[PDB]
Amino acid sequence: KLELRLKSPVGAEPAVYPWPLPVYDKHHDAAHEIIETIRWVCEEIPDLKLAMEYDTKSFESMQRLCDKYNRAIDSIHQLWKGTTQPMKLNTRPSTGLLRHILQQVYNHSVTDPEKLNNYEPFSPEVYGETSFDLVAQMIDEIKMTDDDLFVDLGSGVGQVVLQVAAATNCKHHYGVEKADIPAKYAETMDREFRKWMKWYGKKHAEYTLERGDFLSEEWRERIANTSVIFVNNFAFGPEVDHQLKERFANMKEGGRIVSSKPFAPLNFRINSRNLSDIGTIMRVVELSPLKGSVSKPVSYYLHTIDRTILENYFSSLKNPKLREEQEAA
Ligand SMILES: CC(C)N(CCCNC(=O)Nc1ccc(C(C)(C)C)cc1)C[C@H]1O[C@@H](n2ccc3c(N)ncnc32)[C@H](O)[C@@H]1O
Ligand SMILES: CC(C)N(CCCNC(=O)Nc1ccc(C(C)(C)C)cc1)C[C@H]1O[C@@H](n2ccc3c(N)ncnc32)[C@H](O)[C@@H]1O
Image (cartoon, rainbow, N blue to C red; front, side, top):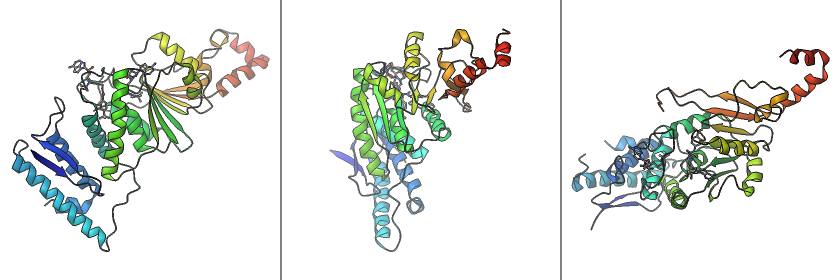
């Protein structure tokens, strides 16, 4: 048996790979994961990048790369023992590193990715090469603080929950998934994610990947108490979207829902016939699309619970002037 090992930059257990190096799918294999890990650790640590003064099918050539990386790591650990300051260990991963870490967690967790169903509207042979970016855009645009609770509704193997948990301060992040196959992989994604984040010396916020149905009664109260919801509802039917509207109607003021299809018209106009529709209690905006993203770019929608829309309508009805105007129609 032959092996390649990469040392952890913070002294966790080394990553070990058998030779020949495994292929994970049509676009991912262990040789590129190794090269990319080396590259990313070099971004974490300048002196390492400096000190790194390649045929992926030659063992010797790949061992010469690993050896070189490992010797460089040893010398950086020595440097840290001296007066030099160690790497800050309390930090979150940059977006780029997080993309790599999640690909790596997915590689080791999702043993047969063909079993998982494609998430419309994204490409099926792409592994989040745009969904990852959209979520990244949202993480930046949506201020989240430690008083927030986050849910991804229908969370698959947990790819979005783990991204968001790596990046934000929400008190807790949840994913709820209904199907056996994705739920089982989520169990492993969790394990591998905790392990690889330790390996790179990075922190995440608390999260839980749970098995459940988000239309169940247990999730009624839980949706009600969530302040940020992500849901890729583009392919949902009108019955399921309707049931979600019922749940969203119980959210607290300021609650936010980001979706791929809006749950209410963007120019909702409140009157006697639409008094009970969800548009009476939320602002809806079309978010800024991300250049370099086909499906015409991917559009996405932010809803904010705001009952003052409804308060003003009722106040307007008490005013006989405004009341007469509305009765123009
Ligand atoms: C091969 C994998 C990626 N699989 C998609 C599984 C769901 N997507 C998913 O997990 N994306 C994802 C994965 C990782 C990340 C992170 C990087 C961790 C953030 C982010 C997003 C393939 C599914 O699409 C189908 N598929 C594959 C190729 C094919 C085809 N050319 N045309 C039609 N459908 C096809 C296949 O039947 C499976 O249902
Ligand atoms: C397409 C959605 C619905 N989902 C994707 C899983 C990965 N998460 C994901 O893509 N999140 C996400 C990505 C991007 C965005 C934005 C772009 C920001 C809008 C928002 C959210 C699919 C999973 O949801 C599950 N699902 C569907 C209904 C069902 C149910 N009632 N309770 C439990 N889980 C259920 C289904 O079994 C799949 O595993």
